[PDB]
Structure formats: structure tokens, C-alpha cells
Amino acid sequence: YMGWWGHMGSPPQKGIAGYTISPFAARPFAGVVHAAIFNTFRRTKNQALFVILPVSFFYYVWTQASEKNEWLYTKAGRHELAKAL
Amino acid sequence: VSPKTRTSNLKNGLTIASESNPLVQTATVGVWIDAGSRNENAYNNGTAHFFEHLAFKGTDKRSQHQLELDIENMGGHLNAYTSRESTVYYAKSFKDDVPKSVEILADILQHSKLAESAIDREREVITRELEEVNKQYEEVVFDHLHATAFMNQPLGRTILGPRENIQTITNTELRKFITENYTADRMVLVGAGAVDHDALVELAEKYFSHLPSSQSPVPLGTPIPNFVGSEVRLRDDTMPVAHIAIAVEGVSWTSEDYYTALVAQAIIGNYDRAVGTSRHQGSRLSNIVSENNLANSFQSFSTSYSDTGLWGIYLTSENTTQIDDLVHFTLKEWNRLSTSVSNLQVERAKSQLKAGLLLSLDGTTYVAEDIGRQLTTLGRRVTPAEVEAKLEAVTEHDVRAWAQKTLYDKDIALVGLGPIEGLYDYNRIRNDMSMMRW
């Protein structure tokens, strides 16, 4: 499923003209400030839910579990600990 | 020793230049103009080429049909071509048909109708030319090469112009173009073959005396190009042959390095598998390419303009899995113009060029073309003795110094057409412009 240069396995290409300029002719950091602010904001905004939802859920689960565990091993939690074991 | 080129002027500033050959019976007279597509802007791009069509479409006297008949009756033919910086209109005839041909040329240049009906008719003919150049691969490659090397500059434009302009060119803008550009101080009347100079000067006084002079007459061959390292890829898997051009910014006609660039070009030279002698050529690249079947052909070029040029090579190959080797070996041969060339290659190339520059001129049309080109680019015909001296002045140090500032580690303009999957990206091509071992 992969060939090599000259016979890579692409379907025949026709009709596309590609253009580019030399690395010495270009400004490598052209539009960097716009990218760093607006492009990163767009990309992050669109992925935020997929990170926030599972992270927030599992952090809440952990927080509840760790606080209960801590409470069961205090004096106040003696009775509830006795039942839990 | 060839006969001397005679040169005279008229009062308007039209140059007449002639070289007689009493051994031939035909003559080429014509008008070389220091003007071409590069004189258009973006709005009227295509005008100069449009005019070339209309020049043969009828004048104030002779109609289209009468024009056809008049030339048929002369016996010879008329021909024209428009380039970026030069336009030519010439007539090949019999010895004694020269006054007829001068009269017809003077007529089609000064007194052409440019009738709205004819503009409208050619507007379709030229539109069809846009879809049929597509077949002339060498031309496709070189027009993309100019377009990218001189990106958004006048030398980068095509001669045909965009489709949009073809539909909007008016007789007004045609007339304006030829009034601004076809002036006497930009024109040379040239005769080669069976022509008398004194006869030709009289014919010039008779037909081209009422030509406008420009307000500010600069010398012939007077022009700022900013080369762009860049690439155009026109991949087409269905073509069997890849066509690739690689060029750097080269030298103008009047550069001090003009001969050094020609010698460097001759060290790489040309190759064509179809010619029998090509397998035995002395050029290193020739030997590599022929032994390994890397290419069907390659042709080194050094194209000059008034203020810039392009120096490079044009390759054709069916070996689609070894395009990388072909490009690699070609650019490593260019590296050697900087690192390795000695008196061995330089003196061999000089020998070959001393003859080559004279051999090229083997007929009246070639002679006329040489007088016209040199007069419109340099302002004078350079004698073979001067040419022999300028070539002799080229040393190996000159070639090395030129290559080190023009080729070594420089940006290239690169165009590939056809099955070019194996042509690597710009960086890997441009990395072969230097050698890490040096």
C-alpha cells in the first residue's frame, strides 16, 4: 500500500498546479502573532469540551472518594468506617 | 572574414544596417523593434501579440486579400514574431524584389487599418491559441519559468496575455501601443544577403521617413527585476515524458559577465539521445546522463534581457524513477563550476564557442536576425574579432568567480511538467546548489 518515489501508488494526478517560494525568499514568521492568538484560540475553543468533560468528571469522582476516605478515618467517621468494613 | 556590416541613420533616428553576400540570390529585409510584451501593463497585456495578427489583416490601401496577393506575387514570404523585449517583421524575397518588400513592410507597420470587424474576428483566433500552446511543452515550461522567476513583474507576463484582455482589447489601445512604442529611434531596418546598403537607405528615406520620433530618445537596448526563488509543479501522470527547467538569475546583454556566462553554459552543454555523436561528448553531465539513461535530452541556456537574464537547463526524461538522480547529478555539475573547473574545461568550452558563435549564422535570415538582435540590444554590431577577444579574455578564475556569485548556494526557479512525482520538494533541490564537502 505504499510504493516509492515515482510510483508511490497515487491515483493518476492531473490538473493541479502547485506553487511555492524559497525558504530564503519567505518570512518564516509571517503572520505569527495572528496565528499565536487567533488561530490557537479557534483550535482550542473547538476541542475544549472533549478535554473538559472527562477531566472534570474524573476529578470530581476522585475528590469525592478521597474526601470520604479521609472522613472515614477520623473519629467522627468511626461508625461509618465500622460498617464499611 | 565576413563582409563589414554597414550602418546608417535617417533624420528621425531610424537605423539602417546591412550585410551583403554576393554569393546568394535571396535577401532578408526587415524591421527589428526594441519593444515587446514587456512594454505593456497588466490591463493591455496581450496587445503587442494582438497587433502582430492585425498587421496582416489589411492596410488603408491594400485590403486583406490584396495584401495576400501582393506577397504571393513578390514570390517570397513575410514573417513576424513578438517576444518579451523585441518585435520583428521581415520579408524574404528575391534580389530584385527588395523594394516591393520594403514597401509592404512600411505599409503594414504605419498604415494598418485595425478595423473593429477584424479585431472581433481575431479575438476568437487568439482565444483558441490559449488552448493549444498546451501541447508545446517546452513553451509551457518556459512560460511558467518566467512567470515564477519574475513573479508579478512585467518580464513574468506571457506574450498572449490573459483571456480577459483578449476579450477587451480595442483598436484604440492597439493604436496607442504602436504609436508609443514603434518609434524611429527604437527601430532598425535590416538587410542581409543580396542587398545594396545604399539602395536600402534610399528605400528607408522613401517609406520610413514619416515615422514619429520618441520625446526622450534613449540609446538602443536601454531597459528593476527582482528574481523569486520558487517552483511551479504541473504534475500530469498521463504524460510519458517529464519536462523540467531549473534556472537562476543570469546576465543581461551588456553585463561584464556575458561571455563568462556563455562559457559556463558551454561547459555543461547539451545532450540528445537521438543524435549519434551525443554519447561521445566531453561534458561530464553528458557522460553521466548517457551512461545511466537518465534523460532523453538536456539543453543548457543563458537567456539575456536588457536588465536581467535566466541561466539554467531544460531536461526531458522518461526515466520517472530516477528524476532525483538526474536533478542531483545536474546540480552537482553546476557545483563544479564553483569548486573544480580549471583551464581544462574552460579552454575546451572557449574553443567550441569561438566557432559556435560564427557557425550559427549560416543563412540570410540568421544574419539578419543577428544584425537586428545586436543592434537592438547593444546599439552596435559586434565584429567577430571583438567577440574573439572577449571570449579569449575569459579565464578559469572568471568562471569560478562568476559561478560562486551566481550559482553557488543560490535560489532557483524550478518548473516541472508531466510525471514528476519523483522530483523532490524545493528544499532538497535547492540543497544541491552547494556541496557540504567544499
Image: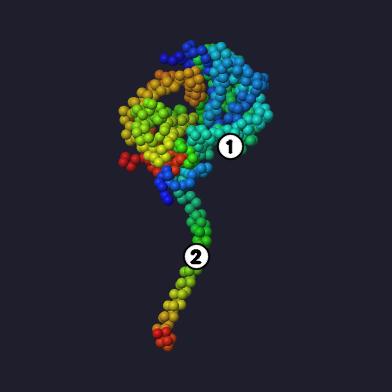
The residue shown at (54%, 23%) is B32
Is B267 placed above or below A21 here? above
The residue shown at (41%, 14%) is B1
Q: Name the residue that disc number 2 marks.
A: A50
The residue shown at (45%, 33%) is B310
Q: Name the residue that disc number 1 marks.
A: B162
The chain holding disc 2 is A
Please name whichever residue, B395 or A68, is drawn nearer the observer in this view of the structure. Answer: A68
Disc 2 crowd, CA 10 A, few/some/many (<14, 14-19, 20+): few
The percent position of residue B338, horizontal first and vertical second, equals 35, 35
* Three-letter residue code for mark 1: Pro
The percent position of residue B92, horizontal first and vertical second, equals 54, 18
Quarter occupied by the C terminus of chain A: bottom left
Is A45 placed above or below B397 here? below
The percent position of residue B438, horizontal first and vertical second, equals 32, 40
Disc 1 crowd, CA 10 A, few/some/many (<14, 14-19, 20+): some
Please name whichever residue, A58 or A41, is drawn nearer the observer in this view of the structure. Answer: A58
Please name whichever residue, B320 or A78, is drawn nearer the observer in this view of the structure. Answer: B320
Is B76 placed above or below B290 here? above
Callout 2: SS? helix
